[PDB]
Amino acid sequence: VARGWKRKCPLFGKGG
Amino acid sequence: VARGWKRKCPLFGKGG
Image (cartoon, rainbow over all chains, first blue to last red):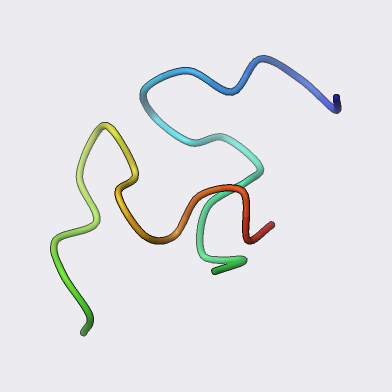
């Protein structure tokens, strides 16, 4: 894992 | 836009 996939998707977001 | 990119990224998540 990169960071901490929690609420406010920091990295794993727009990626879709 | 697909859904509603808010807190708990529903769609735009792991995609990244």
